[PDB]
Amino acid sequence: IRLEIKDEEARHLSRKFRDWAYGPVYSSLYDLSMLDTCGEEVSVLEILVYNSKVENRHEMLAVEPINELLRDKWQKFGAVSFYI
Amino acid sequence: MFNRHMLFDIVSRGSTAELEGFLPFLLAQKKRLTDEEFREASTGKTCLTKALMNLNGGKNDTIPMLIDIAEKTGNLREFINSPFRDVYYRGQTALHIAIERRCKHYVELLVEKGADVHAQARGRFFQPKDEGGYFYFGELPLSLAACTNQPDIVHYL
């Protein structure tokens, strides 16, 4: 997930990026390549929840993008699905 | 070349030898550096503002040269003091950018040629987080230099 390669030829497969660095504020950029598979077979996040029976899944959800990725779709779908 | 797209590139390239003969070229076609077209129609980003964005180790030799070309046209208080014309990055000048990237050598160059100290970067980006912006500093370059953990500009201002 934290994959940023300096080699500049294996760059198109790098995962972490740096958008803009205006002083104190850094703008990182994570790819949702397999995290939220919209029209694909099966996702990373689905196996984190539906398939993995390992104890470490509590820690494994506490990685950087997924703590904010889950807050994305919660803010868009939580208030709607509750009201229904 | 003779267009704007060549000029906005080479400044980011930082090759002053590829910018030769343009000061007599404005003598021919009577054009100012910030007349209509050598400035972004969406934002207002000029050549000097573009010069401070892309840096070569924090050094671009076009920066005194763009002031030099502006001196012959007579826009030293205009080519430096032209803020952004957009809404989101509204009011940001080249003085705000040079303080931002800690070009202490270039901060001294702007004011000596004439720079508005009290230019307010009052854009929607420069608002606090409750208002929709990402970074707040009170819209002032003196306050900006204090917010960038740099007292050296603070001594200079």
Image: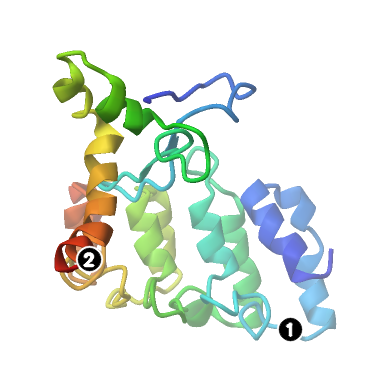
Instruction: List the single residue furthest toward the front.
Output: A84
Q: Which dot, 1 or 2, sits closer to the camera?
A: 2
- For residue A6, above or below residue B141: above
Numbered tag placed on residue A3 in the rendering:
none
**Left/right of residue B43 with respect to residue B111 in the rendered view:** right
- For residue A19, above or below residue B9: above
**Left/right of residue A43 with respect to residue A57 in the rendered view:** right
Q: Quadrant of residue B21?
A: bottom right
Look at 14% across and 24% down and name the residue there: A58
Q: Chain of mark 1?
A: B
The residue singled out by tag 2 in the image is A80
The residue singled out by tag 1 in the image is B31
Instruction: List x then y, in percent, for residue B32.
Output: 67, 82
Q: Callout 1, which amino acid?
A: Lys
**Left/right of residue B147 with respect to residue B30 in the rendered view:** left
In depth, the one of B67 and A26 nearer the eye is A26
**Left/right of residue B63 with respect to residue A78 in the rendered view:** right
Instruction: Count the numbered circles shown.
Output: 2
Q: Would residue A16 be seen by someone viewing this image from the given angle?
A: yes
In depth, the one of B5 and A82 nearer the eye is A82
Q: Secondary structure at mark 2?
A: helix
Instruction: List x then y, in percent, for residue A75.
Output: 22, 58
In depth, the one of B18 and B42 nearer the eye is B42
Q: Quadrant of residue B7?
A: bottom right
- For residue B149, above or below residue B145: above
Q: Residues within 10 Å of mark 2 (few under 14, many from 20)?
A: few
Using the rendered image, report if marks 1 and 2 lie on a common chain. Answer: no
In the rendered image, the quadrant that contains the C terminus of chain B is bottom left
Q: Callout 2, which amino acid?
A: Val
